[PDB]
Image 1 (cartoon, chains in turn red, yellow):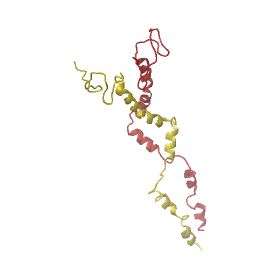
Image 2 (cartoon, chains in turn orange, blue):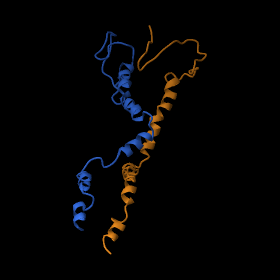
Image 3 (spheres, one colour):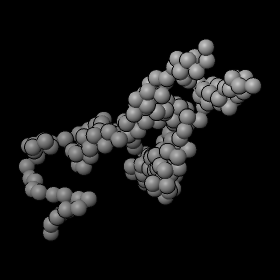
Image 4 (cartoon, chains in turn green, red):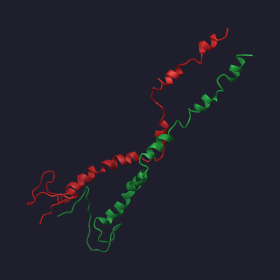
Amino acid sequence: VSRGVILGYPDGTFRGTQNLTRYEAAIIIARLLDQMRDGETPAGMTAEDMTALQNAIQELAADLAALGVRVSDLEANAVSKDDFARLEARIEEVAAA
Amino acid sequence: VSRGVILGYPDGTFRGTQNLTRYEAAIIIARLLDQMRDGETPAGMTAEDMTALQNAIQELAADLAALGVRVSDLEANAVSKDDFARLEARIEEVAAA
């Protein structure tokens, strides 16, 4: 009666083989899109393999390790703190001749 | 002989169109589930897009940055350490009138 197909399914109109917009002929039933689909669908997959790229645990460790306070109210904070002098450098010295 | 279908495939019993438990009629062959399936399957996809939400690198940076020692044996530790006085404040002072 009506292929209908709306969710997880779709339809429109068809007849003489000829071709179709971004569809043409090519038996490729769902493949007509499923192909380019899976092709694109491999996006996540792509990133995924890379996200993997083995390095299991190692990656995490590296990331964590690379972690610090690399930055700086720090400096500002670290630099500032450093900024010192050997405790009261001059002060200390002054405090006894 | 027997559609069987057990792994990546399934079956039970069918006949007069009428309907079916959580299946009813609706030609929707695999779609009978594949639809609701993909629908649900989009779960990961959903989180995924959000996990993405662009912010590539930025998110990581932000997360890392937001990293600290935000917490506290710290306090306990930081607070404690702070807790100080300007080195030997009173002590220092005492040490010369």
